[PDB]
Structures are given as structure tokens and as C-alpha cells.
Length: 23
Length: 427
Image (cartoon, rainbow over all chains, first blue to last red; front, side, top):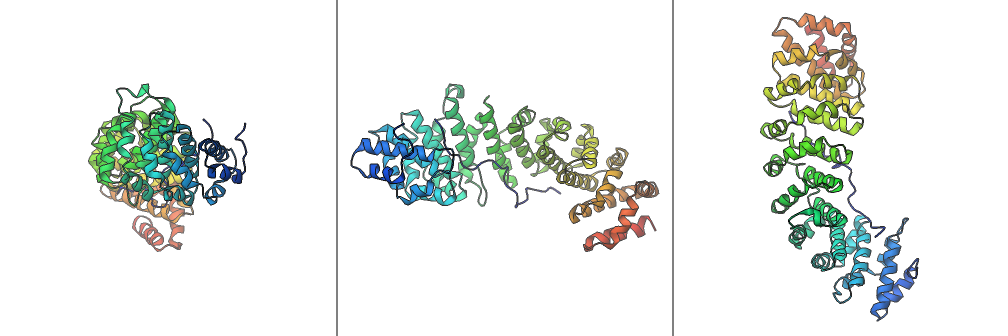
């Protein structure tokens, strides 16, 4: 049967936040 | 050059002056400290008690430049640890940033978008708090244009990114009505031509589909699957990755939901995905295949028709171990739900030898998986009276030697299943 995402894995590894260092 | 590398105490002196221009200059100096390449002194700024001052500066419609500098400063504080983000929220920044979404100054509006993205990005609680304060309407209003192409590139990327954070995280997942509110705009972004927008749009969708069938349905009913399949064949890895993530999530749903993925032509992309030079892509693709082979016999048949079985033999034969293990799963699922004919086809493609070779792995779970698959294959062989032809095939590639040895295994399920196989088809 179907196996969903393991609860102990992240959601893809994309950064959650971003610091602005230039304009 | 005049606001470069101030001490925190000088920044405090300026901000505590009763002079708006002195305050502007000190705020900019703070912004530059918080924007430097290395070790921004976020905690020093927080400890100096500067956050409430920055937040008040957000409300100074009369002085747009200090609005922008404080917005930028607060954005960077909010980009840090959960505690640092909490300090910004505690200062009342959320409603202040939301008010700024309406600013006539694009660069200020954009900055507020960015800041809200960092806040929502901290987790479910701040995500939902940003939503309760009413961020979604004004955010979506910024995208209510005839053609997204007229918007500044960076501006559109920031909006898309912040939206994806509003779609992100579980326990709990975002509010149903918020997701419904966001989806149409998200579908439109998914058709834009900028790689960054496309990547983040796909990530959002992958977040939304990472949950129970009802969540998946909300997305699938918007008719995005064909577009996702298209993005699945893109040349850009940062687009392919979240596209594949989303497709994989969708096929964890119902067979009917999985069928939409098949109908959209997804399987034709898998010869490439299952041989993709990026390890993670092969793993994700094989995992996806395993959930497809866990479906209906007519869905297994389409896997067959698309010539995907040899590709599964391939990854079972040689791949990163994690991938090989997803392949093992795909095989057990296949053999558990497949017809006799489909199962014999599997053996004809050469599944047996690479299956046996993986039995020498020191991972208790995959061994169970493989043993179960063998039992399934034998069962199909019984209905054909060709159990002996299978036993020899297994014997000749050194499979019997491995199974015999498995009779002495730590795990109980292992040696019982192996013991059973021996005194049923060998011995």
C-alpha cells in the first residue's frame, strides 16, 4: 500500500528565512 | 560611507535623539550592520532594545526613507533564530508590516512582503498569526494585474516566496480557507516564465500536497497536474525537484488522484528521472514509482507499457542504497497487487538476481521487503506449476545461499520468512 512522507524527514530542504545583504 | 560600521551604542544614541534625521541615519547604520556578510550582531541589536523603535518607525508615513531602513533592519532580525524572529513579532511588527503592503513606494511594500515571509517562515504558529492579522488579501492584491510580466522581477519573486511560506509547514497545516484563498493566484504563478517564480510556486504546491487526501484534492481539482508534469520535464534542477516532490505527494493519495498523474503523461518522463545524475531525483522518482505500483492492476499495466520495469531493474541493480531501497518497495508493491502475467513479466525482465544481491545488505527492513516480494513471486509461480523453475533461478544466482543464512537472523520476522521459504520451495 501507499507510503507517505516519513515524519522524520524535512519538506525538501529549502531555506525557511532570508537575510537581505544587498539592494 | 558615513553610516558604515557604527557601534551599537552610537546607533542607540542616534535613535534616542529627538531628531528624525539623526534617527534616520542611525537606523540606516543599524541596517548596514545587519546586512554585512558575516556574523550580523542581531542579539546585540535586540538587547539594546531597538526593536520597538524600529516598529514605530514603520508607521512614519511622513518619512518613507526611515520606513524602508527600519523595514530592512527588522527583516534581517526576523531572518535569524526562532527567538530572534519572536522578538520582532513581540514588538508588534506584524500589523505594522501589513499596513506597509499598501505603501505607494514599491521598494517599501516589497520589504514588508519580505519581512512577513521571514515571520511566516518560522513555523505554523507565526504563519497562522500572520494570517489572522489579515496578510493574505493585501498580498494577493499586489498580484491582481492583467499580466505578471509588468511587475518588477525581484518584486514578483519576493511575493511568490512569501506566499509559499504561507503554504508551508504541518501540525497543523495552513487553514483550509486560507489555502483556498491563495490557490488561484498560485495556479497563475505556476504558469509564469521566471525560473525562480516557478521553483517557489512548485515548492508551495508540494507543501500543499504533503498531507491527507483532502488536501491533495484541493490542489488536484484546480487542474494543475498537467502543468506540474510539464515542469517535471524542465531542464532546471531547482524546478524539477519541487515539481517531482509535488507529483510524488499527489500519488500518495487515492488511485483516482494517482490516475490524474498518469493521464497527464507523467510516466513518460520517468526513463530520465530514474537515471537522473542527481541522487535525490532518482530516490524521489523511485519512491513515486513505488506508490504507483501500489495502485490498481490497470495502473501497474501502464507502468509496464511505458517500459518502466527495466528501469526499476536498473535502479535495483545499481543506485544509491536509499534509492535501491525505494526500488525494493516498488517491487513488493508491484508483486503484491499485480496479476500473474504482470508478475512473470517482472521475472523475465531480470528482477530476481539484483533482488537476491540486495539480500546481503545490513538493513533489516529492506530484507523483509525483499523476502515478502519473493514470497509473492513464488505464489504466482504456484499458479503456474513453475515453482521449480524459480527455485533454480534463485539457486543459480546465489540466492539460496543468502536465504539459508537468513534463518539465523536477529529479527524474528526475517528468519521466520526465510525459514518458511526454505522448507516450502527448497529443502
